[PDB]
Length: 291
Ligand code: HEM
Image (cartoon, rainbow, N blue to C red; front, side, top):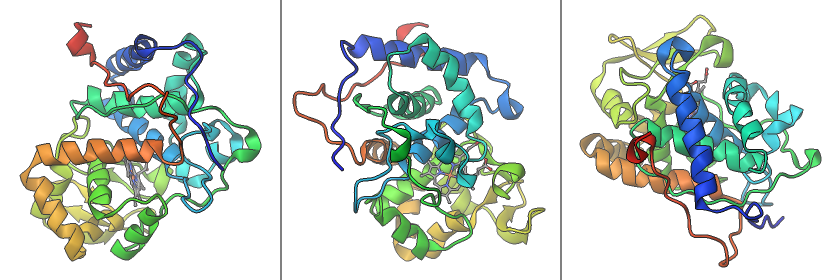
């Protein structure tokens, strides 16, 4: 496969900035979801799960085809709970029927991070919806019950190296795990709907205790009321990953700069951009626009 980026016919920066402004205004408004966490966390988890099916060996999966819209990917056990992020974005797709599904699912993630006080993420338009038979089979998304060796081997299929993997995993400060979705339960820190380096600081400063939860799965619990997954806890058990965790814990700006670069790379894997294509757009936040 080659997947060439094609701009939605006739659309420019200001059209996309209107879809972003509409996702951000609805984030402001539906602030009660999941005990007042808001939809920001499930929207960046939707943007990474539609991108994480990519396989570098044959160019299949990835964000291009917007295939989550199909039953097979939608009903994938690893995608339980993302139906909430889909339902949120659906009125917005009726308001802007011209934007592709992959472009909308991925911009939902960019909007959520920037509106949660994260770094600016450059975003590129051009994904094209593809047929139901291009939909990737289930089982390409990662297990939580595993170690640092599995994590490194997994992220190599998306050719993400160590620093990219540690920066990307910093998004687990956001939101929480839910027992009925994944068999895990609990938050990862205090500020779980503001984007900060808190995941790293909690992983270095809490007194973590291994326990089984109500689903019979193990997780790392702390006195404070926080939890970490086995794969999260892996980042301080591996010596290469641990020097990077310490770097981000001492420097949130370096974390922002590296998360920005890696999240964009994750959203654009498997897509060729012609050089006639527009440069990546930097969207303004509501606040920047006075809205
Ligand atoms: C080895 C990698 C990863 C594994 C095994 C993993 C696993 C999980 C699991 C089990 C949950 C809880 C789901 C639930 O019960 O609702 C979760 C939540 C979440 N994940 Fe990951 N994750 C990984 C990588 C990432 C990456 C790379 C991102 C983002 C760049 C990400 C973002 C999120 C977000 C934001 C949540 C919170 C969702 C919410 O509050 O509803 N994860 N993850």
